[PDB]
Structure formats: C-alpha cells, structure tokens
Length: 5
Length: 5
Length: 231
Length: 231
Ligand SMILES: N=C(N)c1cc(-c2ccccc2)c(CNC(=O)c2cccc3c2OCC3)s1
Ligand SMILES: N=C(N)c1cc(-c2ccccc2)c(CNC(=O)c2cccc3c2OCC3)s1
Ligand SMILES: N=C(N)c1cc(-c2ccccc2)c(CNC(=O)c2cccc3c2OCC3)s1
Ligand SMILES: N=C(N)c1cc(-c2ccccc2)c(CNC(=O)c2cccc3c2OCC3)s1
Ligand SMILES: [Cl-]
Ligand SMILES: [Cl-]
Ligand SMILES: [Mg+2]
Ligand SMILES: [Mg+2]
Ligand SMILES: [Mg+2]
Ligand SMILES: [Mg+2]
Image 1 (cartoon, each protein chain N blue to C red):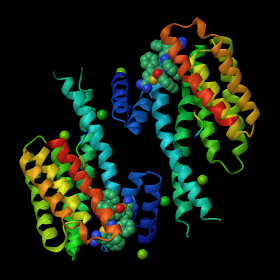
Image 2: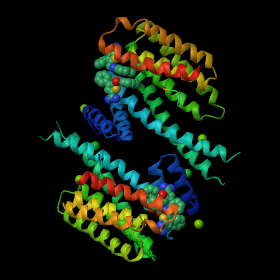
Image 3: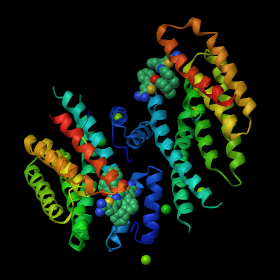
Image 4: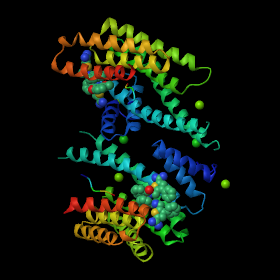
C-alpha cells in the first residue's frame, strides 16, 4: 500500500 | 453494464 | 516530424514504455511516427498502434458521452456546455481522421497478407464508427455506410483466410455486431452475428493448443457478454 | 491567452465540466486561465485549481516512477529509456513551474485571509516537493528546503488561525508529514507530526456539526493510514 497525500 | 468492444 | 528524426526501432521501444507508463497519447504519437517511416507493421506493432489509439479515443469518447448527457439535460445555462462538448468532439474527430489517414496513406494498400489487410479494415470500420457516434449532419449516413463497407470487406476476407477462432476475426465480429446494434439500428443483425460467431468459434476450439485456446475464449467471452445484455 | 479571451465565469464552469468528464488537463488549463484574470479565488475555485493540477501531475509522477524503475533495472539497452524518462520528467517540471508561477504571480501576495494564504503556501510546498521527487543535481537541496519553508509557514499560520479539525490544516499536516518521511529522510519527524495532528483533531471532534465531522474524519483517516504503514 502506498502512503497517502 | 456497457456492451463490450 | 515531429517523430521524423527518431529511429523506427526507438519509436517502437518508446511506445512499449509509454504503454507501461499508461501514457497513451505519447504511445499513439510514437506509433504514428513508426507508421510514417513507410514500412509495413508486424503483428505486435499493429497491436501497439491499435491499443494506443483505442485508449486515446476511448478517453475522448467517455468524456463526450458525459458532456452530451449534461448538454441534453440542459435542453430539457449559456453556451458553455455546447462549446466544451464541441471542443472535445472536434479533438475526437481529429484523432479519428488521423488514424483513418494512416490507414489510407498507406497501411491498407501496402498490406499484402490477408491477416494484415483484415486488421486495418477492421480499424477503418472502428474509426468511422467513432465518427458516427458523434455525427449529426449531412454526412452521418455516408459515415455509417463507410463503416459498414470496411467491416464487411474485412469479414469477407477473414472468412476465407482465417479460422473462426482467430482472435482478430473474433474482435472484428464483436465490433461489427456492436455497430449493427447501436449505430445502424439493426439489433437482430447484431444478435445474429454475435451468435453465429460465438457458435462457430466454439465448434473449432477442439483444434487449438493451450495458448490459442486462451486467446480465443478471451474474446468469445465478450461476445457472450453482449448477447447476455441484448437478449 | 490561450484562455485570455474567455470569461472568468465561463472558465470556472468549464473547469467543473472537465472534472465531470475526467479531462484534467483541460480542467487545469481552464483554472490557469481563471487565475490569470487577476482576481482572488474563492474556496471552491481554489479547490478546483488544486484538484486539476493534482490529477495532471499525479499522472506524470506515476509515469515517471514506472520509467525510473525500468531505467534503474536497465542499469543493474540504448538511450531510449533515459530519453523517455527525461521527456516525462521535463513535462512534469514544467507543470510544477507553471503552478509555482501562478502562486508567485500573484496568488500568494494577494491572499489576505489566513485560510487563503495557508491554502496557497501548502500548494507551494507540494509542488516544490514534486520537484524534489525528481531532482538529482545541485538544486535538490535548495528545492527541499524551499518546500520545508513553505510548509512550515503554512503550519505556523494554520495553528494560529484555524482549528485543529480544519480540513485544509489536516491536509497540510498530512503532506508535510509525507515530505518529512520520504523527501527529508526524517521519518520520526513524519510520525510525530501525523500523530500529534491526528490526536489534536480527535480531541476537537466534539465541537463539530455533522457535516464538519464528516469533513474532518475523512482526512484524519489518511493520517491513520500513514501511521499504520510507518509503524
Ligand atoms: N503491447 C500490447 N498491448 C500487445 C502486444 C501484442 C503482441 C502481439 C504479437 C506478438 C507480441 C505481442 C498483443 C496481442 N494482442 C493481445 O494480447 C490482446 C489481448 C486481449 C484483448 C485484445 C488483444 O489485442 C486487441 C484486443 S497486445
Ligand atoms: N494466428 C493467430 N492465432 C495469432 C498469431 C499471433 C502472432 C504472434 C506473434 C507473432 C505474429 C503473430 C497472435 C498474437 N496474439 C494476438 O494477436 C492476440 C492474442 C490474444 C487476443 C487477441 C489477439 O489479437 C487480438 C485479440 S494470435
Ligand atoms: N470540484 C471539487 N473537486 C471540489 C469542490 C469543493 C467545494 C468547496 C467549497 C464550496 C463548494 C465546493 C471541494 C472541497 N474539497 C473536498 O470536498 C475534498 C474532499 C476530500 C478530499 C479533499 C477535498 O479537497 C482536497 C482534498 S472539492
Ligand atoms: N472552515 C471549514 N471547515 C470549511 C469551510 C468550507 C467552505 C465551504 C463553502 C464556502 C466557503 C468555505 C469548506 C468546504 N470544504 C472543503 O474545503 C473540504 C471538505 C472536505 C474535505 C476537504 C476540504 O478541503 C480540503 C479537504 S470546509
Ligand atoms: Cl471550450
Ligand atoms: Cl523521448
Ligand atoms: Mg532509420
Ligand atoms: Mg461538431
Ligand atoms: Mg470579463
Ligand atoms: Mg532531467
């Protein structure tokens, strides 16, 4: 899972 | 559902 | 230009990179450049060309449908919805004209093999079909009949020269069937074509290797999906 | 130009149509045109500007990451991978420079309210951050420190002038935290900021209407997601 912005 | 091509 | 100074092999390589990057506008520009080198295209190269423009025009068509629905509701608010729908429509028509231009100058005439000629005539049908989706004026009928003629010549060649499981033949039949259903107002023609195509492919699956079986059944499923929707 | 001849209101209306059509490049061009009229932007208009360029640069960044991974594997094949990665990178830098240009000429200086100034300083941090993602040369350090300075000034203003549940304040903290984690090599700073921001918002949820509660908890979930990934 990719970190969120 | 949309027909396929 | 603007791709005229790049090597053909480099354009193909960059098309494949653009596909992995989901940069389909770049991909289509690279493949246009490759076509314009003047040499015939291989099967993989034809597929790259088709995938690139399919995705480009697909985004345009999806946008057009959204805007057209908004425009129609607004006619049941100023010129802006019509203006912007027209802008997208014009860009879409330009892409279709570009593809048809590549086919006419000179992919189709230089396609010796049946398999290559069928591939390009099918594309010709598709891009006249996309033009028909947005056509409203005096040329709608000419555009529709041009799509039919291209599809039918492709069908005639595919039936003589390709087996009924060939995936390009199946994709041609799928799209000609959709043309009949939603462009030509011929839903029984559409259903009849999808059914005969599906059944004739089913009956020749026994002849296929494991790899070819997968190729064929993938496209047969699309025919079944449309029959399910339509009946 | 090229949007100089269109009415401001028409540009805003067409930005909203482009968003519904998922035509984010058009949306960004329309909103650039709206900014260039020279009037301050409303909250909705600021959100339209931010969403448009986020999606444009998001696609470019995603493509760049794909190409950079391919380039790196190819260094573990000719100049084509590097050339095409550089092409995407240059286009990405141009978009970032365009956004930073709008902020400097003259959105930030004309933003009287704290809420407007915070919004634009946060965007300034983001677009220097996107430049830092691809920077490799002598200006990487200047770019990183410029992002930090913009984010920190935004934090300072947001803490004095906005409640800890304000969604723009929470989105600023989320992105400054990610900056710390993956740009500045300061993962403990990143974790500390995400945690304090989350906890201070939690403690003021009791003050919110039903609508504001939904706004705040939506962004708090993103902070939690990153803490979950990082610890
Ligand atoms: N880069 C690409 N996209 C492709 C490269 C090759 C290729 C061909 C020959 C030799 C090497 C590669 C492709 C062959 N078509 C497919 O697999 C395919 C699969 C599902 C559906 C459709 C398909 O075609 C149109 C509709 S697609
Ligand atoms: N005669 C055949 N049956 C094929 C020969 C080659 C071929 C391969 C390498 C080199 C030259 C030709 C094929 C490559 N696969 C496709 O094109 C393909 C595969 C899956 C699905 C679809 C496809 O096309 C549209 C839809 S299929
Ligand atoms: N057209 C649009 N996309 C928007 C119009 C308005 C708007 C503002 C004021 C008045 C009217 C409309 C928006 C307010 N932001 C959101 O809802 C939002 C929701 C989830 C996540 C984020 C959000 O912002 C950035 C991150 S976004
Ligand atoms: N002071 C506040 N709390 C807000 C005032 C207004 C406002 C509305 C209309 C007119 C003027 C201001 C808001 C509009 N919503 C957003 O911007 C928003 C909503 C959900 C999520 C996010 C959002 O932004 C980034 C992330 S939030
Ligand atoms: Cl327009
Ligand atoms: Cl390139
Ligand atoms: Mg050469
Ligand atoms: Mg028109
Ligand atoms: Mg005016
Ligand atoms: Mg560079």
